[PDB]
Image 1 (cartoon, helix red, strand yellow):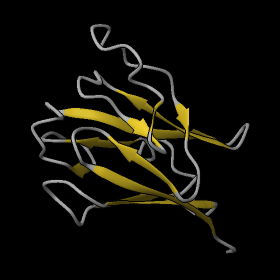
Image 2 (cartoon, one colour; image 1 turned 90 degrees about the vertical axis):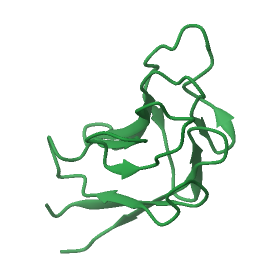
Image 3 (spheres, helix red, strand yellow; image 1 turned 30 degrees about the horizontal axis):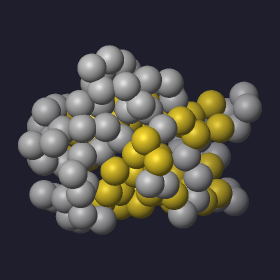
Length: 122
């Protein structure tokens, strides 16, 4: 580790108090996993998310941070905007949406996680 830093915090769900962060130098450990019950990184045990709603993974090539919607039954809205669950019946995995500092995700009825991204001079 040692490059950049992303931090997230569950603001309203059946697990208020879960936070997720990682460095831009993390490879197979970076891709976060927000979900109800599973190997996911955030435990949002809300019926809205059968198992996993969404996650995050970014690129250091174009320095971009985007999240995806794994079977977005309820849907994952970024900054109050359904960016990856635009098609219900489709339940498509969706394409990675780029998140930003001060953003906000909602993968259910009220489960909303704060999106923060800060650097680190090491």
